[PDB]
Image (cartoon, rainbow, N blue to C red):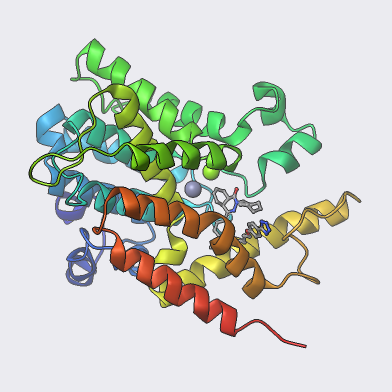
Length: 337
Ligand SMILES: COc1ccc(C2=NN(C3CCCCCC3)C(=O)[C@@H]3CC=CC[C@H]23)cc1OCCCCOc1ccc(-c2nnn[nH]2)cc1
Ligand SMILES: [Mg+2]
Ligand SMILES: [Zn+2]
C-alpha cells in the first residue's frame, strides 16, 4: 500500500524512497519529501526516522498507533502558515535525528532520550498561528490569557502534543512503564520550552559551560554523567535543529528565508490593520532580508553553532563551513551606498 513502507499513501513510492536515501544526512531535501508524500512530510519523516532507529520495536508501538498519532499531529500544523507548518517540524525532527548520530554523541543517550528529543522536535511548533508570542500578548489573545504571557506558544505546543495522545488509537506511549513516561514527559517539556528565543542566551551560556568542562571517554565520546548535563545537551540540540536553516545548502536556506519573511510580513499586515506599531522585521515596505539574515547569523546562529561545534569538535566542521559560506552569500547581496 506504501502506507506500510512509508507511512503515507503516495503514488511516487519510487521518488520518495530516493529522497529518503538521505534520511541520515544534513543534505536531505524535505521540500522534495513533501512533494512526494502528498504534502505529509512530518508523518513521513517521523516514520522513516522511527524505522531507521528501531523505536517502534523498542517501545512496542504499533504502526497503526504511530501513523494515527502522526497524521493527527500533522493536521494540527496550519498549512496556511508560511513557515511554522509541518514542513518546518519535519525539518527539525530530521535535523535532530542527524544531530543525535554525531559521532562524539552517538553512544551517549538512551533510547528513551532519543525518543524524547525526536518527539519534541515533531511537536515543538504544533498549532502555531503564524504570529509571535509578543503579538499574542499585545492582542489580548485567548492563548496569552490561558498562559499568563509566559512562553505562550511553546506551552500551547506541548499541551496540544500531549493532548493528542488521548485520541482514538493515538497513544504511542501506552507500552512504556509509568516511570519511562514520567521521564520522557519531563524531558519533552524541557526541550520544547527551550525553543523559546527568550531563553536562547541562557541555553547558550549553559552550552558554553558544557564546553569549558567537557570530558571525553578514551574513544572520543562525550561523557555526560547526570541528567542535568544530558538534558542540557539535548535541549541545545533541539534548539540548534530549530536554528539550522542557515547551515543547510544555499538552495534550501533561501526557501526557508522566503517563508520566514512571508510569515513576518503576514504578521505586520495584521499589525497595520489593527493600527499597532509594526514589529521589527515585519514591515514588507522597509525590511532588508539580506542584512537581516546576516544579523541573525552574526548574533544568534553562528555563536550557537560555533559553541556546538566546540562541544563536538570536529564533528560539526562542515556545518560551520556551510554557515560561513551562506553568511557570505547573503552579505554579498546587501544593497550598497
Ligand atoms: C530563515 O531565517 C529565520 C529563521 C527563523 C527565525 C526566527 N526568529 N525568531 C526571532 C525573531 C525576533 C527577532 C530576531 C530574533 C529571533 C524567532 O523567535 C523564531 C521562532 C523560533 C526560533 C527562531 C525563529 C528568523 C529567521 O530569519 C529572520 C531574520 C532574523 C533577524 O535576526 C536578527 C537577530 C539579531 C540581530 C541583532 N542585531 N544587533 N543585535 N542583534 C539582528 C537580526
Ligand atoms: Mg516555536
Ligand atoms: Zn520551530
